[PDB]
Each structure stands twice: as structure tokens, then as C-alpha cells.
Image: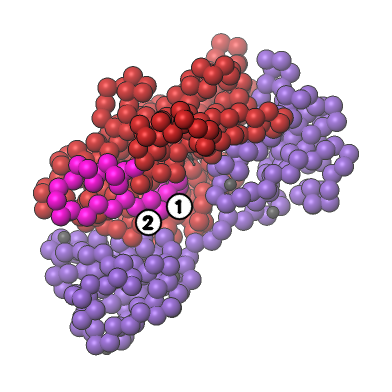
Chain colours: A red, B purple
Amino acid sequence: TTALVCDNGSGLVKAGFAGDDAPRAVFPSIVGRPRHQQKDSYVGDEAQSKRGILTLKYPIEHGIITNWDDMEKIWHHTFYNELRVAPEEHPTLLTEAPLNPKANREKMTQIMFETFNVPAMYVAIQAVLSLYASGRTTGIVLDSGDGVTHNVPIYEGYALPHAIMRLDLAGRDLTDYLMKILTERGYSFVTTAEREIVRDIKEKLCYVALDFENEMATAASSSSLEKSYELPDGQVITIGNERFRCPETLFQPSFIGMESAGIHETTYNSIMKCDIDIRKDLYANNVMSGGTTMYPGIADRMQKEITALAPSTMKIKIIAPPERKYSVWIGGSILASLSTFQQMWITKQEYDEAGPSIVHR
Amino acid sequence: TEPTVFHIQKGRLVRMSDPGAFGRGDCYLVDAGPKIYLWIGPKSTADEKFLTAASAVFKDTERKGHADIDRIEGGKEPEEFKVLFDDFQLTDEDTEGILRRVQLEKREYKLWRVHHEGDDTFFAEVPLSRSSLRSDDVYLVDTWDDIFVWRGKDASAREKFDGTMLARRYDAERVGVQEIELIEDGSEPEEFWRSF
Ligand SMILES: Nc1ncnc2c1ncn2[C@@H]1O[C@H](COP(=O)(O)OP(=O)(O)OP(=O)(O)O)[C@@H](O)[C@H]1O
Ligand SMILES: [Ca+2]
Ligand SMILES: [Ca+2]
Ligand SMILES: [Ca+2]
Ligand SMILES: [Ca+2]
Ligand SMILES: [Ca+2]
Ligand SMILES: [Ca+2]
Ligand SMILES: [Ca+2]
């Protein structure tokens, strides 16, 4: 029988079958309940479309599962509605954020065995899956998703927790900022389809400037940086410096009023928290993963910023795999396919004997 | 040719009887004692890269972390690495990987109803059947590679707008171009009916 792979993110669930090269189910990690006036909950696209009558909640906050009642609804939807499988017939691989608390991993394990009756399970660290999928045991992962951005240094297969940095700024903040600056141009984005337009513009037209101030000057002096997005009805929205002001927020969090270092400085700070003897390997192996690393120009900008900060004789290299939008899921798909990993799966009988703490051993 | 070489092949480590040739489409794990080398072919796939890295950590851990792991990019071998072998050779060998493109049978397509009447708006899955196509609403047929948006003869302009935007977001979340076909009630092409 075939393993299932579920990469639960703050904004999106990515799920599918081990051995597939892409997740076949991708849907919003949102649970809607019609509170205070027999189906009692909605998930995903259906839920987000009915915001006017549902109370919507995100069960995963900054990568960490926080609302377990709603997370169970997400997993039930994943198994039965999206994948249309019987969970008791499939070993299931789940992913977890950096610095996930032990009690959190234990509750994930309890729910998989006691609620869904999976025959076996495994929990993998998201950043390690991405690093291995790039063919590396050592490097520093920049994982930027919808709710959180982490820098995760990894040495010969093991994450270095004291040097992990967390920045509570990622794709949802960029969507909200683009919506703000487009509303300042006199547009209105209130309906579900209008909010999808902002998301589509962000993912299709935005880019990271190599030099922000020079790019602003170019945008002020000519229309060569303008690009247009055509709506289904033939309307056209044209943007110029909004294209690169939006993701500039990753490097300048003050654009949205956040008093935090940008992603180049958090990367440098993370490397500086590691022992000097491994920093050379981290500088040469900055691996990007996650949907918010997909902006054209981001690798070249990171290369420039890190080079400005790094010591003499260090080699700076940013790795941006073309598949990095879903590199966590793809890493899990590979893992759950590999013969030599089968011995490391937790079986239901082991859970019955040992309880949830078996997930650490 | 002193180190032990494992050729990653279809999700397994295969110990090479006579190492030295390295194919650009593949990955290899080279156990040279105090040093473990990952040899990453420039045309290799993620499943091959992953097994090499994971296996190197396992072998190092087996020796309580006492080996240095080095990553080699195929075609750019250092002098240290080439001299380990009697006759180091770079070839075009490429073993096919284990990952497969997503494919849907017809019993797996999904059908989505799009409704928008004032502030009465929603998406909703409905049973994949020609019966579900109501002429006053819009419907999305998801066949993975192709998305058909069927616009009822009596559907509102807002529902047609919403259906196309939803189809755009499906395409955006799936790697590679998915074709979006806008279909009009009463002039459906044969390609559309096959999905039922
Ligand atoms: N091509 C693109 N350009 C810019 N942003 C993109 C692109 N594709 C997806 N995104 C953004 O990536 C985010 C989703 O990424 P991902 O699936 O990695 O996050 P997640 O796992 O749900 O969240 P997190 O990792 O923060 O818990 C969304 O904000 C989405 O708009
Ligand atoms: Ca994620
Ligand atoms: Ca020989
Ligand atoms: Ca190969
Ligand atoms: Ca070691
Ligand atoms: Ca209607
Ligand atoms: Ca098809
Ligand atoms: Ca696509």
C-alpha cells in the first residue's frame, strides 16, 4: 500500500501520495463554522468563499498547530474529501515547523493513531526535507511561507535550534500590503474574487529589486517598469513600483510598521550564532524554500546583501531550486517512498505499547 | 578506486562492484573513510539528491558523527576527489527516478458550483454529473491538467467573473501551465463532455 504525505502550512495544506512529483491537493488551511445560526463546519475554498456567514479560523499560527479541534477538521477533509482515501489503510507522513514543542508533536501523533487509526506515521522537520531535496546535509534554509519566515541552520543532517531565527512576516503580510497600496490607487478589493486578483497580481507581477532606491528612481522617470494584469472581464490594472515595493517588505519590515530586521539580516544573524568553524559551509549553501521565496530577483538580492555582510574569503551562494514552492512536500514524497526509511516509521503497535512519546525516540 | 561507492538507483543504494564512472543524470554516495562525499549529478532529480544526502547522514551517524561530509557537484570535482579512482570518468548515464507526474482518472475529476447573488456568494463541491450543471450558475470541472469553466445561459456576470478567477487560482497553485477553457452552455466542445 501507498503512503500519504501532508505538509500542513499556516496558509495552505499541501497533500498527496508518496511518489508523486507534486501535491495533488492544495487548499487554504481555514476552517469555517456557522456559529450562532447538520453539517457543522467547512474547510478550504468552500469555507473562505462563505466568510459572510461563517466564522473563519486558521488552526496553524506561524507554522505551529494551535487549534486542535479545527486541525482535526483539516485532516479529515484532507483524507476523505480531497484525497478520497481511508486513512486506516495508509501510513501517513506529516511535517512540522522548526522548534515545534514536544507536546505538540505528541498530540499530532495521538490524533493520527487514535482519531484516524493510521497504521504507521512519521513526523519530519520541514526545513530538513527541503535541504535534503537539494542534495545537501549542511546549509541554512530560508523558509518563507504564508505566515512565518524561518532561518534554519542545519549541520550534517541536524537542525541547530539555538541559531534558528523566526520572523513573523511572510506571504499573507505581502498580500495585505499589496492590497493596501492598490487601494491607495483607488481600487476596492472586498469580494472573494477581488481578493484573488490581489493574490494573482502578487504572484505574477511582483519582483525583488536588486537596488531598491535605484529601482524607485527608474520607476519615477519612465514607464519601463510598468506591467499589466487583465481581469476576466477585460479590465486592466497596471502597476509600476508596486511590483517591487511589495516584496521589498521582506528586506525592510518597516514598510508595514514592523520593527524587525529584514530577511538578509536575519540570515546573517543566524549564521553568526553558529560556531565559526561551520559558517563557511552555511554561507555557500543558503537554500530557499517556500512560496514567498518565488519572487523573481530574490536570490540575486540575497546574494548581494549577504556578500556585503560576510567576511573576506567566504564564498556566498544562494540556491533557489525551481521546485522550491513545494520543496517541503516533495521531500516528504521522496522520504515516504524510500525503502531504507521504513524502519523509522512509528507503527500503531508501538504507539499502543509506548504512547505518544515514541515520536521522539 | 579505494573508497566504497553507492550508485543511487530507483530509490535504493546499489554498491558499485567497480567504481570510477559517474553519470551526469545520477547521484552517488562515496564512503572514503574519514570523508563521505555526496556526488550530485547536474541532471539528477530530487529523489536521487534526497537519498544521497539522507544516506550520508545515516552513515555518519552510524560512525557517531566522526566523518566529514563533502558535497561534490558533478563535472566540477576537486583534485582530491578524482585521484581516489584508478580512472575517474564522467558519463551521460541517467537512471530514471522514482517520482511520477500527477495523473487523474476520470472518476477523480471534481465539479464546483459558483454562486453569487448580491451578498449571497459561495463556492461548493457538487457531484460530478451532467445533471448538476444548472443553467443559472457557473461550474468548474477540474481534470488536473485542464480546467473547464462552464457558464450557464442564465448565470450572472458576477458568477462568470468568479468562476474564471477561481480557475486562475487553481492554475497558479499547480506547477506547469494548466489550460483554462471557458465553455458556454449550449456550445460545449466534445473535449468537455468526455470528462463526464
Ligand atoms: N510565485 C509566487 N510569488 C510570490 N508568492 C507566492 C508565489 N506562489 C505562492 N506564493 C505565496 O506563498 C504563500 C504560500 O506559501 P507556502 O505554501 O510555502 O506557505 P505555508 O506553508 O502555508 O505557510 P508557513 O510556511 O508560513 O506556515 C502564499 O502567501 C502565496 O501567495
Ligand atoms: Ca510551510
Ligand atoms: Ca576498480
Ligand atoms: Ca537519474
Ligand atoms: Ca560528522
Ligand atoms: Ca446564479
Ligand atoms: Ca486531462
Ligand atoms: Ca499552473
- Foreground residue, A144 or A246? A246
Few, some or many residues within 10 Å of mark 1 (<14, 14–19, 20+) = some
Q: Residue at label 2?
A: A133
Seen in the picture, residue B127 relative to B118 is either above or below; the reply is: below
Task: Decide which of tag 1 and tag 2 comes sooner along the chain.
Answer: 2
The disc numbered 2 marks a residue on which chain?
A: A
Q: Quadrant of the N terminus of chain B?
A: bottom left
Q: Residue at label 1?
A: A323
- Residue farthest to the left, as pictured: A276
- Foreground residue, B10 or A305? A305
Rendered image quadrant of residue B102:
bottom right
The disc numbered 1 marks a residue on which chain?
A: A
Seen in the picture, residue A23 relative to A57 is either above or below; the reply is: below
The residue sitting at 57% across, 16% down in the picture is: A186
Image mark for residue A156: none
The residue sitting at 89% across, 39% down in the picture is: B186
Place of residue A221 in the rendered image (x, y in percent of width and height, measured from the top left): 46, 30
Q: Is residue A339 visible?
A: no
Q: Is mark 1 within 8 Å of ligand 1?
A: no
Circle 2: residue type: Ala
The residue sitting at 43% across, 78% down in the picture is: B92
- Foreground residue, A157 or A144? A144
Distance (Cα) linking label 1 and label 2: 10 Å
Left or right, A214 with reference to A283? right
Rendered image quadrant of residue B89:
bottom left
Marks counted in the figure total 2
SS assignment at label 2: helix
Rendered image quadrant of residue A246:
top left
- Residues in magenta, as a range: A301-330
Place of residue A202 in the rendered image (x, y in percent of width and height, measured from the top left): 51, 34
